[PDB]
Amino acid sequence: EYVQFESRSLLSLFTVGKIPPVDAAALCYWGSRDYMIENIFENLPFWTMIKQTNWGRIAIIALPRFVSDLYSNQDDAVQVIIEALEMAGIIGAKFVSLTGLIPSATDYGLAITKAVANREDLPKITTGHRTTGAAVVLTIKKICEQGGRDLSTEKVGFIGLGSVGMNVLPLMLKCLPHPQEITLCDVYSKLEFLENIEQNLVHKFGFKGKIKLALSKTTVPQEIYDSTLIVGATNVANVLDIMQVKPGTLIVDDSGPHCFSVEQAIKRFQEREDILFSEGGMLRSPFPIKTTVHLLPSVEKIMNNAQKEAVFNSNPFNIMGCAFSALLSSQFEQLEPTVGICDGEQSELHYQILQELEFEAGDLHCEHYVLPAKSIANFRQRFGKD
Amino acid sequence: EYVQFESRSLLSLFTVGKIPPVDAAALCYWGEFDWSRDYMIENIFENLPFWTMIKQTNWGRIAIIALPRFVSDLYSNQDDAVQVIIEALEMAGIIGAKFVSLTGLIPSATDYGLAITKAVANREDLPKITTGHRTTGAAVVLTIKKICEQGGRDLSTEKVGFIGLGSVGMNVLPLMLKCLPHPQEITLCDVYSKLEFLENIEQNLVHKFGFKGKIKLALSKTTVPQEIYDSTLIVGATNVANVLDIMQVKPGTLIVDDSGPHCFSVEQAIKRFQEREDILFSEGGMLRSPFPIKTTVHLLPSVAVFNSNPFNIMGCAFSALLSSQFEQLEPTVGICDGEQSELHYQILQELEFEAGDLHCEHYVLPAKSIANFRQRFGK
């Protein structure tokens, strides 16, 4: 109903006026190889989806590279981003979001902004980490509501304090009830960094509860397993043993790839129903989103599997916060685009606007698995607080 | 060398900045293993225009865009042709074209642009259109001059007969009289119903344009009157095809034709010239640029010109670039005046343009055979 496929090229349809221009854009990537890049991707960006929301249209554009291709050569990645930016500006995008690990790979956009120093015709870029942080805070709120708990009585543990983590933590303290304990986990080198936040926690952000610091290589410290609400924003994967966390624990994670075994989490939740876990960066629009989908005609035949036609069954209300950032920056002057390591306290302005438009976090789900409402209720009955 | 193929779509390459924008555009069609007029339109052309060629000249870049229709599809439904023309015009405006020419029989199919310009009355974002008939007439006059020089003859000593005085012909006749030596005799041929028109042209010849020689009139349905075979230089500008028997023309006769389809049998003329070498015949609307044209070619991935003359270019197609580069070269839409082709002949002369080398469709006339003709029938 809300998803419709298109056999004809979206770019060609736009050039002849058959589809209207978009207001924003989002750049994503894929998951022999050279044959796929030059003869399938053709070293060219691909406009694959259009997301019609109640506040504008964002175009989804996939780069002709993989994540490894992005980490291999930064200049090449910046070049393909510049080409996709030219495409987005031509098709009407006023802002372009860097989804996934594109910010982490390209100096959080700064390198890109160097290559655009010459050009002003190109559209503005944004890492979207402030809207992603607002989405993660909305997910904290939602997972507390679904679990029948309140954030004031929770022990919160952070496993990743990157851009997204440094956007979620102060916004959590500012727009949600303060927990009673906060633990900060990152690699050893970040020690001083964590202590800086520690100061900011007690004196700047105004946290009164206990503050703990913990360091790790690839095995999260047990202090996290002693926490009751876990917030993951780590780029490393599978550092959290989901089968070792205490019962009644709530998990919110924006990491992609995730920091815990997805399948083991699904399995524990299906067997015992003693945990809650969900994505962090997913927003739920109050109105359904009309998604126009154009598959690559080549891969249309290898993905002709009716199961691969599951985008026809995706949630019409869900949208990525990082991708929605471009549309937000286009529709609201006050939501300035984020490139590089920004302050992260202006995420409130995004959290404000998202609440103003009656946005909320997407229903509790992790990748392909949506947590069943009755299992959610069973958890909320077994581990809720009165 | 000067033409190079491109495996990826030109539109996508432009969208990413890998090829620069163009200054003009020209709209063509595919002429006339699957359904020709059905599968090719919906699953091959996808009912969308196709940017197939880029012509980089010394005066700008022209984009070649093929419509998802055939020539018959244009005469079948005028509104459908206008719609696909609007879509191609939007594409051309997106890729940078400031003016767009209608090649081939597109004007005759769209009332010479009038229907299109009526549908765009609301719209100003689209680029302006032009039939390009004035530059085509200038090209035909250049071809008259060139075929007279190659044949060792002068136009003043020629008996010229015109077959069909349509839009292009009403541009060729006065420009010929003004910028070339006046012949001593002019014959005018069209259908019988056309006569008062012909007599009007006769008046314009003697009183307006200042022709002093004899003026003859001849009418026909589908068999050109014997008066045309008594002429020494025949100029064909007819939309009907193969109305002039090339095997019936006198020896030593020069023929210049802009008709597409042609008004004489192409293969019979080629083969007669190869056997006897007693005629000269060539296209009328082809110009030869002083500098080579760089042609970027993108073929339909589903599916030659790659050896064509790098100096040759259609006048109707060059019209859009000319109108883009020169304020004085106004676009032609509808049945306009035939005297402003004069300014186009000017501009072409200033840039040192000339008519394309003597050729008919796929066949280039060998120069030394032309020399044999020019001695056998020179003065």
Image: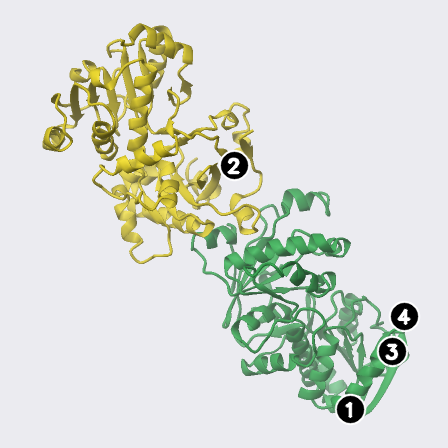
Chain colours: A yellow, B green
- Residue under numbered circle 4: B221
Helix, strand or loop at label 3? It is: loop
| Image point (32%, 15%), residue name | A276
Asked if the residues shown at circle 4 and circle 2 are in contact, with their CB atoms under 8 angstroms apart, the answer is: no
| Image point (73%, 88%), residue name | B155
**Sequence order check, earlier mark of 1 and 3:** 3
- Residue under numbered circle 3: B195
Q: Which is in the foreground here, disc 4 or disc 3? A: 3
- Residue under numbered circle 1: B207
Can you say whether B16 is above or below A162 in the image?
below
- Residue under numbered circle 2: A292
**Sequence order check, earlier mark of 4 and 1:** 1
Q: Position of residue B270 (x, y in %)?
A: 75, 70
Mark 4, Cα crowd under 10 Å, few <14 / some 14-19 / many 20+, is few
Q: Position of residue A30 (x, y in %)?
A: 40, 35
At label 3, which amino acid type do we have? Leu
Q: Position of residue A184 (x, y in %)?
A: 16, 25
Q: Which is in the foreground here, disc 4 or disc 1? A: 1
> Does mark 1 fall on the same chain as mark 4?
yes
At label 4, which amino acid type do we have? Lys
Mark 3, Cα crowd under 10 Å, few <14 / some 14-19 / many 20+, is some
Asked if the residues shown at circle 2 and circle 1 are in contact, with their CB atoms under 8 angstroms apart, the answer is: no
**Sequence order check, earlier mark of 4 and 3:** 3
At label 1, which amino acid type do we have? His
Looking at the image, residue A373 sits to the left or right of residue B109; the answer is left
Question: Foreground: A69 or B339?
Answer: B339
Provide the chain ID for the residue under circle 2: A
Q: CA distance from mark 1 to mark 3?
A: 18 Å
At label 2, which amino acid type do we have? Thr
Provide the chain ID for the residue under circle 4: B
Q: CA distance from mark 2 to mark 1?
A: 66 Å
Can you say whether A248 is above or below B78 in the image?
above
